[PDB]
Image (cartoon, coloured by chain):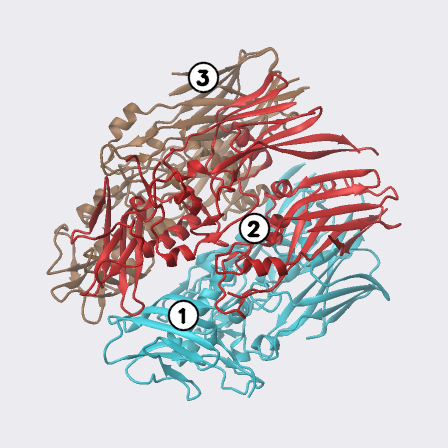
Chain colours: A brown, B cyan, C red
Amino acid sequence: YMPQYISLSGVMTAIASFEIRDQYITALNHLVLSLELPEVKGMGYVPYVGYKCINHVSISSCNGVIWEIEGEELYNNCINNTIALKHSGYSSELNDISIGLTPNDTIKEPSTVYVYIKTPFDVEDTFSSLKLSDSKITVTVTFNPVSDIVIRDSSFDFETFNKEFVYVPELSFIGYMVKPSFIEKPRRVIGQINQPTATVTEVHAATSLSVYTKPYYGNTDNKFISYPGYSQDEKDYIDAYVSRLLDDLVIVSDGPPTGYPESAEIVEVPEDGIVSIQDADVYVKIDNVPDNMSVYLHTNLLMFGTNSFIYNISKKFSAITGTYSDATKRTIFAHISHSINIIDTSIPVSLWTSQRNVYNGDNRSAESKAKDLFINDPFIKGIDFKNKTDIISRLEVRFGNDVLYSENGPISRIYNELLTKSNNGTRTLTFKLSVRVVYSTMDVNHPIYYVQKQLVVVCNDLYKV
Amino acid sequence: YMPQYISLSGVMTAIASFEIRDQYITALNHLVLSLELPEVKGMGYVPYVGYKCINHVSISSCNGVIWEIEGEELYNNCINNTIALKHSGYSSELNDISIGLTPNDTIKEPSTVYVYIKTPFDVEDTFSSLKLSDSKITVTVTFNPVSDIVIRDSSFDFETFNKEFVYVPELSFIGYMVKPSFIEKPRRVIGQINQPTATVTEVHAATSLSVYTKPYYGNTDNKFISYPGYSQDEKDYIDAYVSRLLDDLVIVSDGPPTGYPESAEIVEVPEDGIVSIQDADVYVKIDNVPDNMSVYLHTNLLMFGTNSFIYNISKKFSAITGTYSDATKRTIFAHISHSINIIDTSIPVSLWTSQRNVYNGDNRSAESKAKDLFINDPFIKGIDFKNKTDIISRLEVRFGNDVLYSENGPISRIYNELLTKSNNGTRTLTFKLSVRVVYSTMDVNHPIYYVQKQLVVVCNDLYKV
Amino acid sequence: YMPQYISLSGVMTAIASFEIRDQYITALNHLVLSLELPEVKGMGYVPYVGYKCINHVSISSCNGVIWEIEGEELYNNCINNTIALKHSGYSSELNDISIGLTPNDTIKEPSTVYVYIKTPFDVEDTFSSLKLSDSKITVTVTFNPVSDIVIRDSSFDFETFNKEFVYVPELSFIGYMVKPSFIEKPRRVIGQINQPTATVTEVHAATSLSVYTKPYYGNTDNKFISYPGYSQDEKDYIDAYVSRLLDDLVIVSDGPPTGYPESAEIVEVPEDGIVSIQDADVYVKIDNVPDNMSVYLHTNLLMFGTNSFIYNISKKFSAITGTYSDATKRTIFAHISHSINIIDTSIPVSLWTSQRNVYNGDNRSAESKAKDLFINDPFIKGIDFKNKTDIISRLEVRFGNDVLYSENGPISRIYNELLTKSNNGTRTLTFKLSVRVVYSTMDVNHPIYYVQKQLVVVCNDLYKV
């Protein structure tokens, strides 16, 4: 045999179609989709932008579909491949939130991303390769709306960007100029919103079953206070959020601070430095405060309650130190002691100002609210951005009416992670199927309780080729 | 066959026993121990807390022990498995040193850790699995005292914590409902304190020999000035230590600083900014110093000598810059130029104030001394927390009376690390055995010279199954 | 068989020769070269110092060369082996730029580095090992001048260091006391300076072809403004550079700042804080400025042009905030907003002050210019230190007169990286050969346009053993 890297352009309908047929292409594998990202001008991309574009991939012959996959499941299959993820687009250039100051300003420079479309034909290189029995093979890529792969504020003219944006793809593969086999086709079932059950029918020969949760943000405008950009650690998310709150939390002003809702409770800090918000004490000490000015603490920046308990973000701070700058008229914060977590950074702004909330909700300045970001990432899992919180308390799997498997702790996720050497595993059973979960309880007084959930069940069926 | 994840509770005696016997469990492998950590309340856990709990693991049948291992050797076998180590417990939640301010305050939230008990039955999955010849298999886990897995200060009521703490384990394994083999059983020999020799008797069929050193802290109270928490890099250890010394090293005071031992030599910094401690010059410059106050340098914060040479921590600083805060009455340090290393951060406080020391030793404030931490981690290697310093100068291995192997440089550690793709290797010979080492010399005037050492020799014997 | 780690000293001629012959050494593999680095005294090493020493390695028998490799190609073959690279020497101890203040001061402590000499005899351990047919095997290591592995300033007495420095090597290997095979011998061709073509003649049986670019710094003194040391990320390089410029960029002075060339345009910052450099606005605001002093902005710190466009480093800054220190008489910079990139940090100082430049070029203080570093790393790729910029726009490969392969985008680099699980791949064709590239265009007004390029083509030929 002789291998060759072959690249094809395709027809755009957003859906891209690529036709493979050549007297010398006997076999093929290792599909890679290229995407040309445009120059973005005017007044950031999600991490792994290339994978997030993909809605669905289908491989077909004259006899029909040979193999197909949902975009999220392809991404899940490549999540433990750092190289493939880097090629997708993961950089400060693509993923940091850039700002356009003038209508002619360049926000993002043009770039190319590469999406490794992992197929069952790559497992054993030439041995597993797709053979083309003088057949025409069609590769069909369905794209997600560009709204899903972009993080932006209200100021950005998304309407025009959406109208003008076009997917520019190219398909590459390793062709080979040169026995029956088996292939596993992933099948996905999504449960009804908040329903802790899902069923996979016609299970006759399954190699594995995976169970996970996705948040549903349909009851929101998909706006979040902060986003850390390229820096994706749990701490980066928390630091970006604390940073966004600080300029409204501690104010150096000549008289009571203006520009805040009437619902805002901004209190002058005593000589002591301690402000008491019920049971919580906040120690605030700012250096170089001008003589005509005082230090103020916003005691209800974000507040939620269903006369009952109050989830107050201002109460999550215990110490705030800094120095006022006479030159820039800002407080330059130094050390901050808080108890902010990954869940707080994952609360949509809509849930703070929801109908269930008896309070205003959001007592930030208009300047802070204008800086909020629309995040529509299509592959979010759990109830937080890092999928850190495990919300499944118990899992039961039934084969027919009999209990096939049951667990409390995620011991099936621990084994998945150990056996596949992955740090991003799911509750998986490796070998009809009915899945029932018991969700963990977060307070009814926590805004996160109101994030909608969807149960996802993935089944891999065995097929003869 | 058909695999199944089976979980068992066990009997507590601290020793946990788990009995495996089922007409359908034909074979098993991949043992995982779960541990429920309690809520810690009142006025941090070691990294890889789950592995550090284990004292010994034994697998037995009616015919006796099939396989057994010392806790440290199990940990050593899993040290290159990042996933297994993460599952053990390695997070900011578990490993950062948290503070309890009131008797009802929550220091640590409850959590579950998972310990992968790597056995010779996992190497080739089903091919290497332990077969149960209608036999009852007993798994016995011996636990370390909780004192070993916890990092705390004097203020923490350890007495009550120890009395109330209980190990809550559960054993999981992959069971299989379905020829003679060979297995390697690790055997460990620990030399006499400071003795540079150790012998393994009855060596007939060994697959490998490993040699390493452990510090012995019996001549101390196991108290250290600092600990970096979850951040475990060499730099994190050094930064945590420098940070702890700084508030006693440079003092902004109205008149000579009070609250220090009479042995303390606190000198006013000249207009020049340079203080000379013998041959060492320390440049100290603090901004916003009040008119009624002066800048002072502690010239003997920690001092050790056996009229001879002096190991002085204050002499390890060349430049200290900062700004005094009128609001908090503290110096907010900016840039620090020092020559502090990993060894300095690994010196037990006991060795500064030892009988060999002709000086007081420890001239820190009572506030600083109260913040010291008890560290009893059972798996420490070398003479520093990172096992960075190689203290073996030469190694000789004898098979009977003949020299089997000898080396100066750790070329056997370099090969171990290259061949096993590990960054945490030991001097290893891969294939009676007498090991003799020559230890490197650190100054007799260095407190670290007085850290006791133990030679550890691990031998893997071949057994027929 | 029985394996043994054998170490040999060798003869120094710089060229080291090692002779292997023993009645009991039947086979061998896994060559490791040890190097003793000396104590460096007076008034930093390149990362992977051990690999950068090697110019060439040759393995010979009585019948001639068995296998040989160029130092850069050995390094390229080991670039995806983190362990081997660490052993080479990659630490803060070796790679941070240390300073000697007195002629008796220790800049670097002595150390040992280990260079894994990867050979085709290591692929399948004993199966691929080199068999010694009662033959004498000679290993010849040719070393690079020490000038290549050292990063230093003008103050360092390199002349004396070079005269006194000696390579102290030792060769280790795994010997074994105990059918025809095939081995791939790498062959490298370097094109003429700036020539976008290269040819490999006598190609009869090649397993692969790799193509990459190297900068040629012969038209320079090999001096760069900054180097980040051990911290090697793109951001570390950028931060080190910004940091070096800042003290000349914003000056707090009593009257117009002195000590700058007459070509320097240092402007007083208005009360507004905004300085306009043509189309670019720089916001500069410094706190605690003494009453007798003003804030100045260097508006042409580094300037390049061929009455035309100007590449001005001062125009790459949009916001500079800080606080003046009365104690140290320095500005302590806080937040900086700039558009500095990896290319700016990779510009040799010679290109700023080149004949093509109609401007002075370099309007920094003498203090800043004295801090410049000589970097002679022999394995640099592309036109920047991180090899981030892809300067090949199109690649064409011809086998005879026929086009074997052609590409625009680096799809052959993407496949190399995916198939070899490497994040440091090259445009590679895996299976006479003529390579032609089209280089991308950077502005003629950019100093980087004048960095000389060399096309490198690597061919692996099949040999029978």
Residue C162: quarter of image: bottom right
Tell me where residue B246 appears, x and y as whole percent: 40, 72
Query: Circle 1 sits on which residue?
Result: B319
- Locate residue C78 relative to residue C310 in the image: left or right: right
Query: Circle 3 sits on which residue?
Result: A10
Q: Are labels 3 and 1 on one chain?
A: no
Using the numbered discs, state the Cα–Cα distance from disc 3 to disc 1 in whole angstroms.
64 Å
Examine the rendering and report whether any part of residue A312 can be seen. no
Given this view, does label 3 or label 1 mark the residue nearer the observer? Answer: 1
Examine the rendering and report whether any part of residue C132 can be seen. yes
Using the numbered discs, state the Cα–Cα distance from disc 1 to disc 2 in whole angstroms.
39 Å
Q: Amino acid at mark 1?
A: Ala
Q: Residues within 10 Å of mark 2 (few under 14, many from 20)?
A: some
Given this view, does label 1 or label 2 mark the residue nearer the observer? Answer: 1
Tell me where residue A361 appears, x and y as whole percent: 21, 48
Query: Circle 2 sits on which residue?
Result: B82
Q: Residue at x 44, y 25 (%)?
A: A56
Q: Taking B57 as reference, is C29 above or below it?
A: above
Q: Quick one: C98 or C338, which is closer to the camera?
A: C98
Kindly state the secondary structure of the residue where label 3 is placed.
loop
Q: Residues within 10 Å of mark 1 (few under 14, many from 20)?
A: some
Q: Are marks 1 and 2 in contact (CB under 8 Å)?
A: no
Q: Residue at x 44, y 54 (%)?
A: C372
Given this view, does label 2 or label 3 mark the residue nearer the observer? Answer: 3
Kindly state the secondary structure of the residue where label 1 is placed.
strand
Q: Amino acid at mark 2?
A: Thr
Q: Quick one: A383 or A293, which is closer to the camera?
A: A293
| Location of the N terminus of chain B (image quadrant) | top right
Tell me where residue B51 appears, x and y as whole percent: 58, 59
